[PDB]
Image 1 (tube, rainbow, N blue to C red):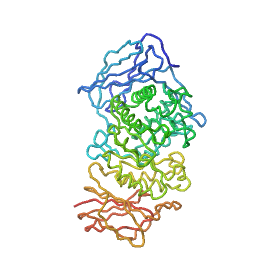
Image 2 (image 1 turned 90 degrees about the horizontal axis):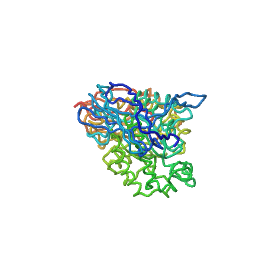
Image 3 (image 1 turned 90 degrees about the vertical axis):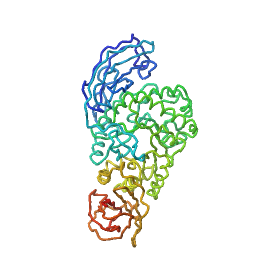
Image 4 (image 1 turned 180 degrees about the vertical axis):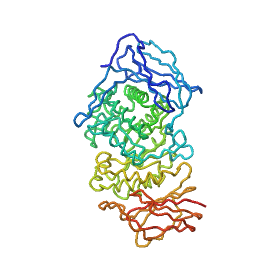
Length: 564
């Protein structure tokens, strides 16, 4: 309770960021107040709210949150944050409709006293922003923005920084975005994470780390990138004796460290922990919910590998059901909600929860991972909601960095996942020690440029099924999608695709190798696409349904337009 107050409840002053702003832009109110509370992060101690109403009958009840300003510097080789001024409270709002809004501020503290402001009027004009990300109503395999444009996530995990903190995101994110990236994932736990809110306590949240997350969210806003926020990771609830980077002994949840829990099993049902967790969800909604650059709220990283002493399937299921209902109810903008598993097929009792809007896969597999991805994507179509391969690599142990410096594994996975029908790319690990130093972003640029003009929401793509290969003395395989106006093929050499010691293909020749016959109606236009240089190699107008395959080293993309 370092931030306690014991004065009669009064609003002292307010600052309004701007009285006119654009659709989906941030409207920020800053509030100085005094009152009686032991913990500004607990709504039973102090409850700040903004009540906003448009001219179309919609009301928004926006929780407010405690804030400390900082000034950042790169002091030697680490980020250093200097506090500026006293902490105070904020309300962060984003308008969905344009036009006029009225709003007022309401505050209640532990004494039961309530105070309110007068009503203020603001004006919202049209903007370029596409809105929040939702599941597509036209094709449940994919995401959309509110404005109807597709959101096809292309990117990687970028879940924490080095000691350089936000200065690492200053480097990684512009490089990702200039190479077709629009997506990343960050971690808000365990307590060592860059953006850890529960750093020293589960009752009070870390204002420095929350400020870093502000900064990175603002950078995503400037770069048109969209972020999955992962609230907790399994390490928090895994005992030392169980390995796999366990952190229970160090986590603030444990009674040894000041928390309410005697053991991780009690996380799911302890009333005090549930209350604190709901307070955390309220803080996250208050501080970040306004942002259309929040793609999704993710409760857990790999909740199935918490301690086996703590995983009770019915309790974990009920907790996800109840927390998804609570989060949705307090989030004025109704962001997407998900969770994840280490077990690649996931847990159907949890994945089928209606309140989880999409499902995920994590998979680290060294052999025949192309087939594994295809199989998992086919399997999870049973849920009739989008599927994000949210973690991918060869080996949780990092063998990738030594065996595949050119990123062929990432390359194979991102092409496989997009052309197998998943909602976006397989999302690599190793952002800091592999993707960036090896400059692997070109793989994403080539894929992004291949799919950029295809509307997955309209094509009614199905996996390619009726094809005949005529290829002699080479074992070529195909992953493909057949749609209303396009067929998209990724062809790979089953031998070479899993061999990583070779230099990046430099395609010079374009000899004839073989053919693929497809069930289509001429005429058609065939585009051959170099998946490494990210460019068209050759274009062929065809009057029959036999598509030549030109020579390639490792893999080749083909885009076929149904003209007839």
